[PDB]
Image (cartoon, rainbow over all chains, first blue to last red; front, side, top):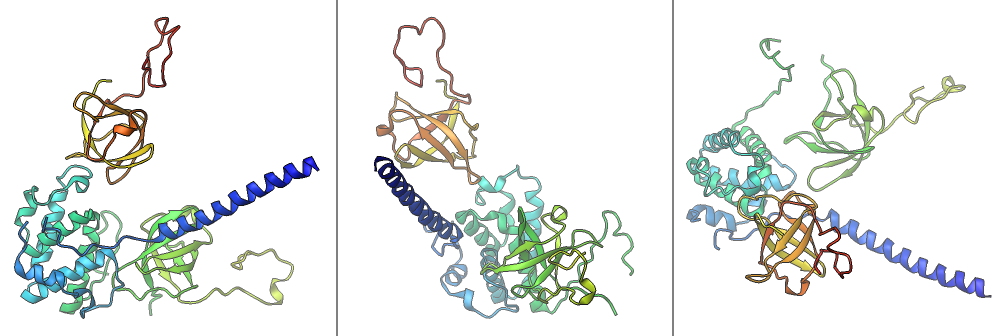
Length: 46
Length: 136
Length: 102
Length: 101
């Protein structure tokens, strides 16, 4: 029981971490593809 | 900087959606070329911008390495002799830090001018030093 | 009476086994999921597959062969056709690549 | 630490990391060197260079006096890696990673 409980705790922590890392990796990939276009502002007026 | 009234008015307008000789896919280097073409079409003279690009290319050969990183077109004397449209576009690029697209913008502007003037350019690729004979 | 290919742009970047092209202004353009030939030499080409057509006009390519010969700035020709490979009873008993090369 | 010249200004501060923007002319900063951020007219804050971007923005890892680091402050470059006192004159003392007692 002690060994299985330790494995259960370890597995849940790893699963949470892996899921969060996967989501953040997807978010970073989405952010990277985004490109900043030309700014249409009165640059001289400054 | 004190841009002219005409360039100021054209800048606010949505020239990006206007009609052009060719339908080039939108891009960062294409917006500046479209702006230059629209500015030059009003006056009717396009060769001035080509001379400005030639002067820019000649001057850039003497500027220090990575001059575009710290380039200040206002302080650079070589760009003081450029036409108002080209100087305005250069300042616009410098504001966005996109002076590395000068070659692409010049290429797109040349393509637009050739399309408008009904000129077809046939690139001839030859070995270095083998350009002497092009009769074939 | 010339074997005129369809140049669509140049090779911009190379990242391992994939590449990105930049179309030359005023060119026909390549179709999605078609095969393209990268002119590694005036007589040699490297096959590639179109995978992405971005808003900027850049094209995502999947290099298939002669990857070591691919360099940035090389010309790219568009065949305009999907991938076709030899098929028939004459291929039995042979080892072939996905491109049909024995 | 001996300063040589200003190499930019503090731009952004995200916890213990910071980013600098280039000074006029982009003097340049050697990679992995120690830079001094002038938090006050007479005090400086140590920083470690870890990233030299194409645009000219330098990535800095703040070492000490982080609470007194603000955007817009001047940054001077030492031009050398981190060096700390060593020898028999340091035995029996309590020091920090920067060598300060």
